[PDB]
Length: 217
Image (tube, rainbow, N blue to C red; front, top):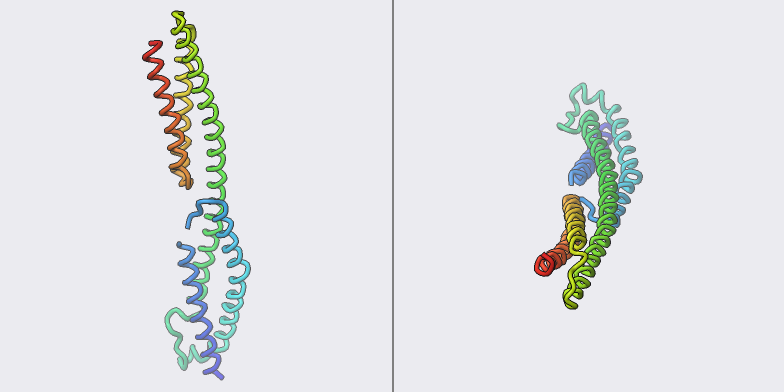
């Protein structure tokens, strides 16, 4: 009777408290490197929020109902409620879980927006890298045509222009290294790979500027 409902109430609240703490700690704990990863985390989150949580909410509210029938024995002292087992303590922990759930949902949308931002930067960097490349190609092509004029004992015509082209590629390569550092800061998983590619264009730049300094300056 009383011993029954007391038993049922304690069994229930014990499992509820274990579950809430378990899930509260799991939320304290997981940053995605890709959309593939964030999609799984989000799915897992929604599965929890929409499938597991309401069942536990039912148990919580059922435990409250069971306790109200025990309240006469509790007040009178026949039953002592262990610390942390009162409907007040269940609600406290339920509240902390609820807060952790909202924070996690906000962190997951914030992570999705970071991933979108990183993608913008990756597109921009790839577009700029093509232009920096073309700029090094145009600088190198002018240089060889001047060198070719320096074969036929003729004077260079585009020295001024080669200088400008190199100063442009330099400016663009510097924008590229800053995009790369923005990727790295954002922990894009290939940040490092992209650094090496930009470092390569920089190497090309130094090679072309050295040749230019040797031949035309």
